[PDB]
Image (tube, grey):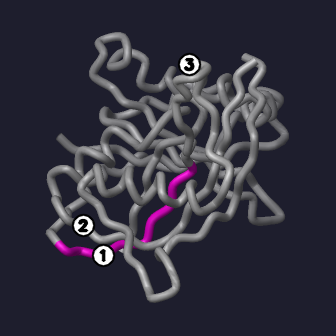
Amino acid sequence: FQMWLTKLVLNPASRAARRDLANPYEMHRTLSKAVSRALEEGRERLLWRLEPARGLEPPVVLVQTLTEPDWSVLDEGYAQVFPPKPFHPALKPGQRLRFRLRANPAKRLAATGKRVALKTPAEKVAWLERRLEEGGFRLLEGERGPWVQILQDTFLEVRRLLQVQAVLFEGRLEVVDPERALATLRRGVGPGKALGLGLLSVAP
């Protein structure tokens, strides 16, 4: 009952990689090949993120899995694989952590039956603040506001036409219920998980 973290540095010379970078869905299809069996048996929850462009490059993909992934499944010259290290999120109560999460802060309109994305940063943060509090976490805060900052906010138009509002949060949170917290990390947070959203990364 642990997890696995993999760091994939994608080779931009690879046409297979360049395709998966353009198409979040085609990236999910590729990634799920490495945990193909446990998915078939419905005992896997695959979560991943494309880490924010820094350089200089090169593109980095962080991949979280419940089962040990077999990265020999990738195309030759697709990515430089780093050994999947057994991740145990040893969580004690009241523990505080830096976090990163690219998520989809939205809401199901009942007037249309559709799931539209929230507009203002004030209501985007309110979504995160709710979602973490549901999941055994709690956003830290100073007398100015919550301890979070939105870094990216892009509208993904994935062809497969999938349309999703991708929002990158980064801030600080406390652990209230360590059991609820662990489960949240395992599940991920909010929609668009097959698009590279949901993975809540935490570090001390």
Up-down relation of residue 63 to residue 195 (above or below): below
Q: Residue at x 38, y 69 (%)?
A: 139
Which amino acid, mark 2?
Val
Mark 2–mark 1 Cα distance, whole angstroms, equals: 6 Å
Between 77 and 154, the one nearer to me in the picture: 154
Q: Counting other residues with Cα less than 10 Å from the Cα at mark 2, is it few (<14), some (14-19), or many (20 or more)?
A: many
Residue 76 sits inside the magenta stretch = no
N-term mark: 2 or 1: 1
Q: Residue at x 37, y 18 (%)?
A: 39
Image quarter of the C terminus: bottom left
Contact between labelled residues 2 and 3, with CB atoms less than 8 Å apart: no
Which amino acid, mark 1?
Arg
The quadrant holding residue 43 is: top left
Q: Residue at x 75, y 55 (%)?
A: 58
Element class at badge 3: loop
Left or right of residue 112: residue 39: left
Task: Read off the residue under disc 3.
Answer: 113
Left or right of residue 181: residue 25: right
Task: Read off the residue under disc 2.
Answer: 175
Which amino acid, mark 3?
Gly
Image quarter of the N terminus: top left
Q: Nearer the viewer, mark 1 or mark 3?
A: 3
Contact between labelled residues 1 and 2, with CB atoms less than 8 Å apart: yes
Q: Nearer the viewer, mark 3 or mark 2?
A: 3
Q: Which residues are magenta?
A: 94-102
N-term mark: 1 or 3: 1
Mark 1–mark 3 Cα distance, whole angstroms, equals: 38 Å
| Residue 89 in picture, x, y percent from top left | 26, 58
The quadrant holding residue 19 is: top right
Instruction: Specify the label residue 96 is tagged with.
Output: 1
Left or right of residue 66: residue 127: right
User: What main secondary structure does the magenta stretch of the protein show?
Assistant: strand
